[PDB]
Amino acid sequence: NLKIVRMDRTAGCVTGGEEIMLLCDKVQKDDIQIRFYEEEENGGVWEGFGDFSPTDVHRQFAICFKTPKYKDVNITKPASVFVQLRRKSDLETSEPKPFLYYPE
Amino acid sequence: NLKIVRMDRTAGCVTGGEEIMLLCDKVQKDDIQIRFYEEEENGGVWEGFGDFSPTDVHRQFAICFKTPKYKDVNITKPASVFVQLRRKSDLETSEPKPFLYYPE
Image 1 (cartoon, helix red, strand yellow):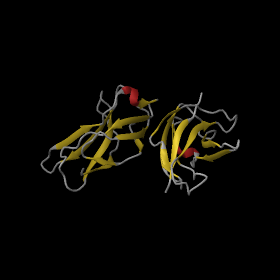
Image 2 (cartoon, rainbow over the protein chains, first blue to last red; image 1 turned 120 degrees about the vertical axis):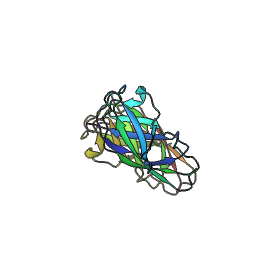
Image 3 (cartoon, each protein chain N blue to C red; image 1 turned 90 degrees about the vertical axis):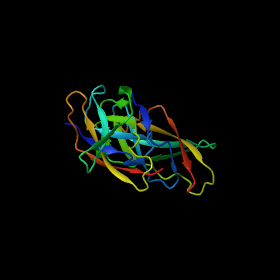
Image 4 (cartoon, one colour; image 1 turned 30 degrees about the vertical axis):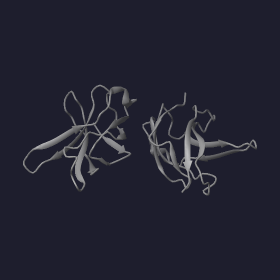
């Protein structure tokens, strides 16, 4: 039942720390994370997490957060990743949205 | 009971048409407008309205909209206005938030 309905930004700088506003279907403020991930060719999986507190969850239907730092702040072209909602308790996830990290 | 909790942008170009995401306390999608206004020195009051449809209201707790065109697209410095929620039915309003229009 997790869904990213809309994000006001779907790209960001590799240094992270940028404010994004996200509209979601209902979530519980203490049982929700925003996971950015990238599947590596070596079977590895990079992940980073949106930076926010339960108070940043707006009436269970939106979240304000800051982006995580991407794995490599020295990329020279954009890196495409995904972002999903994930419940902390049972690790249920939303369908992913594409997200582009760009060089500083 | 109307409240603008957060806006992801509190400035915009005088030409209008720019996407803003707004978090609000509960509203009814068919009984809500976003009014930008400016009190003139001559007792006049400019107003413009955010451009959106009821489907742009997200589960009664957020609204995505486009800014209205400011009264004067030829200003040479920023113009400070206010923005409020207003109920269409009984014209109840939220407390206003400052908003800055800037030259193209």
